[PDB]
Amino acid sequence: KIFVGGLSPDTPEEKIREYFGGFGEVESIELPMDNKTNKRRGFCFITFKEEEPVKKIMEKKYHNVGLSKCEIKVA
Image (tube, rainbow, N blue to C red):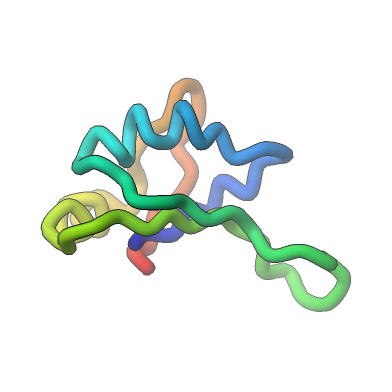
């Protein structure tokens, strides 16, 4: 699974699968946590199936999505 620092108002899942799912079909994704009233730690993860694609994604911590290049620390 991987983690992005896009923490946008709405994780473009469908667009997410287009990119991340592009590295390899996605099983399910993950968005930032709820509440949002403690420390500055809001992002959006995504889980896949095998493990290889993470190797790739993680290899490019800073990719690009649609019109943004959120960060990407595997998860």
